[PDB]
Amino acid sequence: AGITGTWYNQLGSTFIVTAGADGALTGTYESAVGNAESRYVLTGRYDSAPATDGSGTALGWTVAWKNNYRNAHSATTWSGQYVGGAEARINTQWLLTSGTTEANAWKSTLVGHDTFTKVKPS
Amino acid sequence: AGITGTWYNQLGSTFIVTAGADGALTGTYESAVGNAESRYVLTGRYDSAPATDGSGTALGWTVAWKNNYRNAHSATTWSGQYVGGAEARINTQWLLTSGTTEANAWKSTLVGHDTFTKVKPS
Amino acid sequence: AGITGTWYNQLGSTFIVTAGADGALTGTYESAVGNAESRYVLTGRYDSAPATDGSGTALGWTVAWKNNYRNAHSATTWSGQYVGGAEARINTQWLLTSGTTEANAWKSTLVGHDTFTKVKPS
Amino acid sequence: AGITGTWYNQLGSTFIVTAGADGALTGTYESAVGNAESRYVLTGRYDSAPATDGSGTALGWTVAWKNNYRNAHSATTWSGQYVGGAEARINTQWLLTSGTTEANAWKSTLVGHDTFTKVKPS
């Protein structure tokens, strides 16, 4: 429970994630709101025995932007924490790297944040 | 091939990973050499068909810092690219997130970089 | 209008800043609203001829967390952009490096994000 | 106390910087080994009473990529620590932001690292 299920960020993006008993996160990422080729494999890990003091649950997952149809030659990883209950939400920061020449290494990695909630937004 | 194998970073951390045809990354991590008290589960994704024009192969992976010995209440994700050849390496940046309370949420995430080689460092 | 003035983020921090003619940012950052021993010097840079296509105004500044009464032995740099208009704001990502040692250098840099508006939260 | 002076990274970029006794950092950056058009104002802050326990000296500075010649509608912030001695060096992580539209704001900011030494490498 808790992590398992559908999450939406505040810009029309989805991922259905199942959380395993050991600490696994596997699922998909529907980069577009719906369509079977904006969909990408997702896998990750989470603190499957988190503090009880009212801290968040630490987690991260990875998606590589290749599927059956498309390749961005790149990948994103999210790192953050899960908060349950009233405003259940996943707070993250993310890195998105592209394969580059050595020459372009330096401009290879974008950084950002993102918040997913259990209820779609506007 | 290439990616599958054992990897070392400047600080003597190690990880043994398997790269699957799909795009799966599966192995373990160790943040303190010698001992298996720092053996944690790694799962990830990589670009199973990258752009042969000389660019790196994009990938990322996650490690939840909980195993059967200790629990850290935090996870790390690595974003980066793999390069093979005589100087084979994985160059990454990473986010380390600790579960916190609303209060310390601003102190939740560590950022860094990491270069992994097939050869143990001095 | 523009950048020059008073800004607020969600957590009760303010800075007052003057946007110099040729590209300077100078001012003070108060981490606690109405608290004297929490003012620190701010210095920065911004794009003084930003585009005319809707884009934001690139900017960044720095605070070394040392003043008259306190010294954290650390520093933050904010990088982001300014948007004027009805919903004026400065969207930022920040890095916070503390002085560490060789050994502990890995755990030296906090990463995050922040948004300042001309009009207080609640 | 030896922050002021000339600094190099491996991609043949320099900055010259003067560190006042008030926490100020003023200087020039020059992404080209030589070349007036490649010069940009630099301004920052550092910790002017750093601990003497073997920790680096925390600092950061900003550069807005507009000068008397060019405008890149962006700015970099570097955050990091000065390490003196004979292996003297400034270890940083940086954030590069361009002015984007709200639409492209997600790919606004690059991340990376950089090391500077008082001596040009390879």
Image (cartoon, coloured by chain):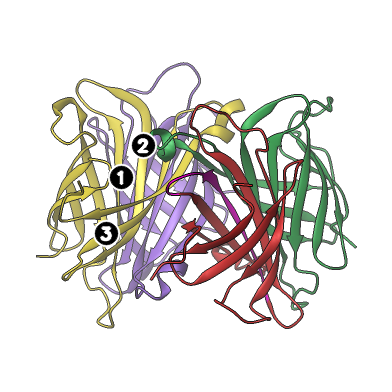
Chain colours: A red, B green, C yellow, D purple
Amino acid at pointer 3: Ile
Give the camera-side residue of B46 and C25: B46
Look at mark 2 in the image and give the residue it sits on: C75
Going from N to C along the chain, the mark reached first, 3 or 1, is 1
Is residue D105 found left or right of C59 in the rendered image? Answer: right
Q: Residue at x 65, y 54 (%)?
A: A61
Amino acid at pointer 1: Thr
Disc 3 element = strand
- Would residue C83 be counted in the magenta stretch? no
Q: Residues within 10 Å of mark 1 (few under 14, many from 20)?
A: many
* Cα distance between the residues tagged 2 and 3: 20 Å
Discs 2, 1 touching: Cβ within 8 Å: yes
Q: Residue at x 76, y 51 (%)?
A: B43
Look at mark 1 in the image and give the residue it sits on: C62
Q: Residue at the far left: name it.
A: C1
Disc 2 element = strand
Disc 1 element = strand
Amino acid at pointer 2: Ala
Examine the rendering and report whether any part of residue A68 can be seen: yes
Is residue A120 found left or right of C85 in the rendered image? Answer: right
Q: Residues within 10 Å of mark 3 (few under 14, many from 20)?
A: many
* Cα distance between the residues tagged 3 and 1: 15 Å
Going from N to C along the chain, the mark reached first, 2 or 1, is 1
Look at mark 3 in the image and give the residue it sits on: C90
- Residue D8 horizontal/vertical position (percent): 49, 49
Circle nearer the viewer, 3 or 1: 3
**Are the residues under marks 2 and 1 on the same chain?**
yes
